[PDB]
Length: 141
Length: 141
Length: 146
Length: 146
Ligand code: HEM
Ligand code: HEM
Ligand code: HEM
Ligand code: HEM
Image (cartoon, rainbow over all chains, first blue to last red; front, side):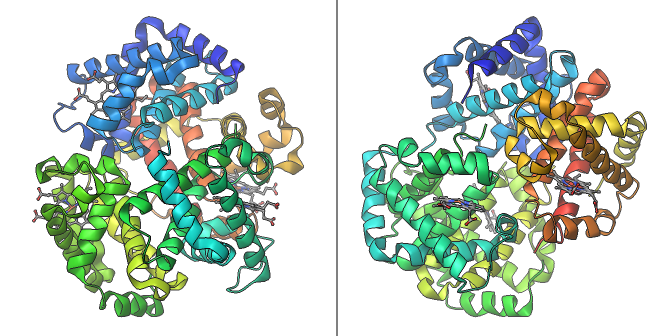
């Protein structure tokens, strides 16, 4: 449950990302694939080698989805509806993996936004990624 | 979210629990403590022996709360308000333990409802116990 | 995997009464009904869009007897689960791309099915010994993943 | 708990730049802020209601030190995390009643803190290596739970 505090935290930290969203998106995914190999099972059609364009491509789509979630923070279910259909009915990633990625997002942003990655913003972003996860996994059954 | 089928499934099954509700909750907790001994870390002040009065009292309390939720399936956050507040701010059980108790409840229901623990009803109770749990964990942060 | 032989014996006594054919189909099918995302691995099985469709689906009963058969062999091998399941783990990782989380889901679904099937006989200490077993199996089936 | 030779070298080399005082208080306070239910164990510590309260709290800083100090010593014995941590494990279970889940959340926060402290030096590979350590530590702390 994003408090106003949180949205402000998220908007600000996400503001500072800006043009590197998709670069961060890409690094989060590869931090994921190396830390939690299990997540690869959902990408058997990807070349998963370092510096791959498939991953940077996917990295960017993930980042754009998040940037879209940040902008429609107050109405994520609707802003994200197409994405939650697709995860529910097509991709069917086990819910556990959303926490793996979110953790890797967080690690990515810490590594990149040292000064903005405050304990408070940390908490907010964590809640923010759980809420996106919950929306993505919303229609699973 | 719970559909009308779900609600019906749960009320039907819970109706069969009827007056066995507290016996069932004590049994679910015993199951939980033995299968998931880490959950005992939350009951250090309890006597955790088969039959203990404390587990029996707590079982009934848990079963009553759940009976209340079934009755309020449409109004859970409000129905379970004291309980989410209590778990958020006082008990503070890590959210992972909800899914362990949920499992043991479901196992207990399955052991006791040979006739009604159909697959659809199973799916329904599982979703129901996930909703309860999301409620009780609502205000954690 | 830490099973006392009070636990060992109880797993053993119960498993002998298990209709591996029937329990297999039940478990796999409930798996697919309760946690529908797991359908993703079974497009090739035909209709799985309803409970009744999944539960009577011949390829599900048939895959379940196969899954449970292999689970059943593991029981003779609680001392060496990793070993018994090395090849299946590789198969699930490299060929099938099964996220090992699924093995956990199935293990719990299985414990529910044994509850349903054995009623009061599926006592809390017997359940506990089955949770150790089912976790042991999910880890062995996960252990060749990379 | 297996690290390749170069992971062990990556882990050991980063850790030699780590100031256990600072990183320990940072990781613990963040734990308390990001997952406030972990506060349940530190009611003796004082007012934990806000991030500044938590990150300034001097008991939190002290404890963070203690925790990361024992974590540091176990890096020395990656090959025997169970033996090394067995006594803390039985303490955390039988005395402190700490849900081992907390050891996992702590490891993830620690990883974030390392990333935040080190920036680009915390490369995907070095994280993966730390994710392994942090998981091994958690499982070693969790092992004598009964
Ligand atoms: C913050 C969490 C996530 C977000 C915002 C997200 C967002 C997206 C977006 C925008 C797409 C593009 C769909 C399209 O238009 O083709 C996608 C696809 C996909 N996602 Fe998710 N996703 C998330 C989590 C995950 C996780 C944790 C996994 C599992 C490791 C996963 C597995 C997949 C797969 C396999 C695809 C299809 C990729 C392809 O074949 O092109 N996702 N996601
Ligand atoms: C469906 C899930 C749950 C329900 C409906 C539930 C319900 C309840 C109820 C009715 C009470 C008593 C409130 C009172 O004192 O008046 C309670 C207390 C408590 N619950 Fe929860 N609970 C759930 C989950 C859990 C889990 C998963 C754990 C830990 C593994 C836990 C730990 C506790 C503890 C420690 C107490 C206080 C016991 C005492 O000191 O007497 N609960 N719960
Ligand atoms: C209790 C753990 C499990 C065991 C012991 C097990 C065992 C097996 C066996 C014996 C086979 C056939 C191997 C062969 O081709 O020779 C198989 C294949 C397969 N398994 Fe698993 N299995 C388990 C769990 C799962 C789960 C939970 C899923 C996913 C929901 C899954 C998905 C599949 C798929 C998609 C195949 C190939 C099906 C086909 O195309 O015929 N398995 N498994
Ligand atoms: C890497 C994981 C951890 C390690 C290595 C660790 C280590 C330690 C050590 C060395 C002590 C004091 C030893 C003693 O006084 O005999 C301690 C005490 C304690 N730990 Fe852990 N700890 C860990 C994680 C956690 C977590 C995540 C929590 C809770 C969120 C926790 C809660 C406590 C508490 C409440 C005490 C007693 C402290 C006191 O009374 O001042 N620990 N821990």
